[PDB]
Image (cartoon, coloured by chain):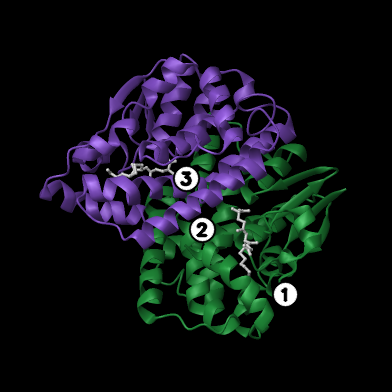
Chain colours: A green, B purple
Amino acid sequence: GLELYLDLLSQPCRAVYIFAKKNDIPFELRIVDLIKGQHLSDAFAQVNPLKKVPALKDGDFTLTESVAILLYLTRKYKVPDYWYPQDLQARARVDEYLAWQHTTLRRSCLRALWHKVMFPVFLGEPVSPQTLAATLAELDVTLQLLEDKFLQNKAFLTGPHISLADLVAITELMHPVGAGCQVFEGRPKLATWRQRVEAAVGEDLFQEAHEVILKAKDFPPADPTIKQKLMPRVLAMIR
Amino acid sequence: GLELYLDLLSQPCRAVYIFAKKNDIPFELRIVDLIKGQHLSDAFAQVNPLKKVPALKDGDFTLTESVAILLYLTRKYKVPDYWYPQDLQARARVDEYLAWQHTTLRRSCLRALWHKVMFPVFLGEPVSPQTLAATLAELDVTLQLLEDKFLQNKAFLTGPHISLADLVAITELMHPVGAGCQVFEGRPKLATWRQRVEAAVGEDLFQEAHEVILKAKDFPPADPTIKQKLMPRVLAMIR
Ligand SMILES: CCCCCCSC[C@H](NC(=O)CC[C@H]([NH3+])C(=O)O)C(=O)NCC(=O)O
Ligand SMILES: CCCCCCSC[C@H](NC(=O)CC[C@H]([NH3+])C(=O)O)C(=O)NCC(=O)O
């Protein structure tokens, strides 16, 4: 009874989805449709009281946080070593990235998607161009840190092989890709890394997991009641 | 040997300090004085190019991020396993808290200190009552989530014993305590939990680690050159 409560629109759900499918981990997929406000229902509030996705249920055990969910599945299903290496220092490099991204690249990628596309297209709320400029400037800074602090001259973020870190980072970078931002343009080292990550994960799986975010621009505007319920949740999300 | 680059004024450094000292981990303490902008010096930039503390140095290996540092020390020095339990679901509970706090409690506790004390006292910069109110209301939301999602009816955040999760949370909560917020007042579940954490950590060590944050209201204001150097760093920290 392993169940993953996911919406492929969100960066953390894509990381969990790709991981579980790549490693042939059997699970029931429960799609929690975020644009319909399904995560705000009483039925989802029973699974996760915080009313957020991804959420994991394994028997009677409930787990939140994509980093925790990824580590739980890594250990329980005994996946290959490269995802979270046995080696003390390689493991630490994975921990370093997973910790760093929460307050930096996660935030920057999220704010890029919402200020450029999901506020004016989906919630019908225009964003000032000064706010959008500042957001994309901050995106540039985090992308530069991704290159200079993590990737540097290596094949992958923490070493010669893909790890949990590369999975979290690539699903994050696809948020502004879906928003139409020039993420990999003029960043050749990131561009070749993306292609290496796509191959390690499986290109077909990569494409499949990113079908929803790549069409975020074509979302019909929200329902006036749905917009009302989602607005404080989104404002607390974007900070 | 092992070197820990710390400033006990900051929440993540206190967590690392308390962990290394409680577990009798031999290290060389390198105080990096934030108030004097020592983290911005060319000498510290060699240790950590990101110019932030805590930073670990163990020979040719350098590590950032307090969560990564705590886990690396956990593993290398074979500390008691209650800090990071071997049981999969208990270890997940620790991972769940460590992941959650980065964008919620860490952020509120850091903003409480800066908007209530460190901007007006140390940097001579007034904060609007509206900004401070917003910050302290968000702190109350995170304190309620700490109680309702994590601590609940248990002795500690993840079960019957202390873990790395309690260490991160207690050092976070002492940031608004040092700013003069009535954190444990009217929250009896948190107040008794604090007493259990202090008892488990050892009261003398707990007090030693918190000597600087409890004196933050009395820091002499920065001169105009130090202020000018620290202001863009502080604004990137306080978004
Ligand atoms: C139509 C879009 C609705 C809102 C945007 C969804 S972004 C995804 C977001 N997920 C989280 O905030 C959990 C983050 C957590 N740190 C993790 O990694 O698991 C969520 O479900 N948040 C939902 C919410 O807070 O309302
Ligand atoms: C009085 C100076 C103001 C410093 C405020 C915060 S001190 C803590 C801060 N450290 C971090 O941002 C690292 C956080 C990281 N997520 C961790 O847990 O280690 C820092 O060294 N920041 C220094 C900087 O960014 O300049």
Residue B69, image x, y percentages: 47, 32
Q: Assign a secondary structure to mark 3.
A: helix
**Residue of label 3:** B106
- The residue most toward the left is B224
Chain of the residue displaying label 1: A
Q: Is residue A43 visible?
A: yes
- The residue most toward the front is B186
Q: Do discs 1 and 3 share a chain? A: no
The image quadrant that residue A142 belongs to is bottom left
The image quadrant that residue A209 belongs to is bottom right
Taking A200 as reference, is A115 above or below it? below
**Picture disc at residue A36:** 1
Taking B161 as reference, is A128 above or below it? below
Inspect the image, locate mark 1, and give the three-letter code of the amino acid beneath it.
Lys
Chain of the residue displaying label 3: B
**Picture disc at residue A184:** none
The residues tagged by marks 2 and 1 sit, at their Cα atoms, a distance apart of 23 Å
Taking A102 as reference, is B219 above or below it? above
**Residue of label 2:** A106
Ligand 1: quadrant of the figure: bottom right
Residue A64, image x, y percentages: 68, 49
Q: Is residue B77 visible?
A: no
Q: How crowded is mark 1: few (under 14 residues within 10 Å), some or many (20 or more)?
A: few
Inspect the image, locate mark 2, and give the three-letter code of the amino acid beneath it.
Arg
Circle nearer the viewer, 3 or 2: 3
Q: Residue at x 47, y 45 (%)?
A: B106
The residues tagged by marks 1 and 3 sit, at their Cα atoms, a distance apart of 31 Å
Q: Which residue is drawn at 68% across and 77% down?
A: A226
Taking A88 as reference, is B234 above or below it? below
Q: Does the residue labelled 2 lie within 8 Å of ligand 1?
A: yes
